[PDB]
Figure 1: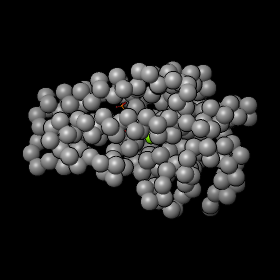
Figure 2: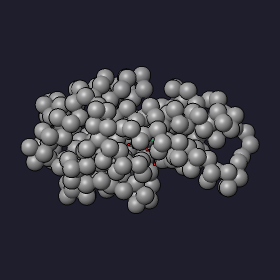
Figure 3: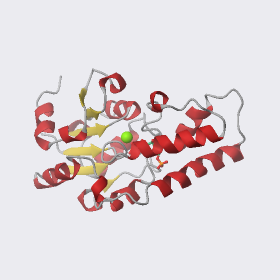
Figure 4: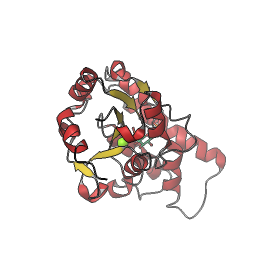
Length: 221
Ligand SMILES: O=P([O-])(O)O[C@@H]1O[C@H](COP(=O)(O)O)[C@@H](O)[C@H](O)[C@H]1O
Ligand SMILES: [Mg+2]
């Protein structure tokens, strides 16, 4: 049976992917880049602060100085951090709190595999910190999503092999990271964005221990 569930945070645990999108779009427009719309944003979900900024800057022909680059990333984060100050337990996505309780009752490890340095703060805002057996620090891995490092680290942090773990993600980059880690991915979002090669659910209410078991018993190979 699987022995661990590796949780992405933003867009899985709570609608915080929407906040990252709005913050990145605002930053981009401030520097005259209007290409960050929902479609383009799918390429930003799951990627690190610096990687997100560079993907946005790639839309421009000229480059910014190292000094401006650093200021831009900080500017976006300062805005994002203000945006999430009022997040509360009421903001936890449907099914997530129950899933955490069910996993603990069944002795299945719970680890956070978020690329966000604001992850710990958000779990505290939502009164979810106590459910996690481990939080993989995104600053410790040598390579961020789509690299599998963070999921491999989350699994190791709870003493479980990635091959015996399920990863929950809402992004293209994150799903790739799960795939290359050896864990089984179950994405949440629309088929047009995440693919038709893995199991995808339309919303988090589908993330029940019953369903994770249903899917796991159906894994290939
Ligand atoms: O989706 P998950 O939880 O990997 O989290 C990811 O965290 C990145 C870095 O976050 P921060 O700027 O707060 O360090 C964000 O750019 C990305 O949009 C978000 O999906
Ligand atoms: Mg996400």
